[PDB]
Length: 52
Length: 53
Image (cartoon, rainbow over the protein chains, first blue to last red):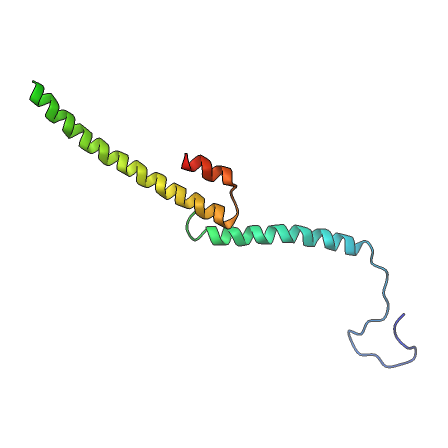
């Protein structure tokens, strides 16, 4: 818990960390898939201009 | 007969040389496309070699 109790807080201020440890893993998997497909899309964007 | 066959053979081989020049132009365009595709990184070196051959 990272707020002092009984105080005023603004919107968007973090309150607790709930130990992700699974969402971090699937986020790493999704980013690993993204790192392949975005450079494939960029290479196809470069090659589609010359009609290769 | 000999002069006639020689003239017709030359007349055939002129257009055949034109078509072989068309083939060379087509293959040069294909090799340039595969060279672009190899420089970008989609194809391997082996497709470039097998187009050059």
